[PDB]
Amino acid sequence: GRMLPQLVCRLVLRCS
């Protein structure tokens, strides 16, 4: 995984 399964939800946290 990593940078794929959370690339979206993180996207939120991408900007976190």
Image: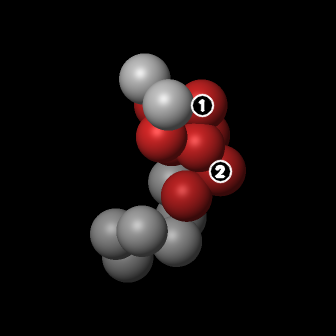
| Residue 16 location (% of width, % of height) | 43, 23
Q: How is the image coloured?
A: secondary structure
Nearer the observer, 2 or 16: 16
Q: Amino acid at mark 2?
A: Val
The residue indicated by pointer 1 is 12
Residue 2 higher or lower than 13, as above or below: below
- Residue at the far top: name it: 16
Residue named by callout 2: 8
Residue type, numbered disc 1: Val
Could you tell me which residue is drawn at 60 percent across and 31 percent down? 12
**Under tag 2, what secondary structure?**
helix
What is the total number of numbered labels drawn onto the structure image? 2
Residue at the image position 51 percent from the left and 54 percent from the top: 6
Q: Quadrant of residue 9?
A: top right
In the rendered image, the residue lying farthest to the left is 2
Q: Nearer the viewer, residue 1 or 3?
A: 3
Marks 2 and 1: in contact by CB < 8 Å? Answer: yes
In this rendering, would 8 be left or right of 15? right
Q: Nearer the viewer, residue 9 or 16?
A: 16
Assign a secondary structure to mark 1.
helix
Tell me how far mark 1 sits from mark 2, CA to CA: 7 Å
Name the image quarter holding the N terminus.
bottom left
Q: Position of residue 14 (x, y in %)?
A: 48, 40
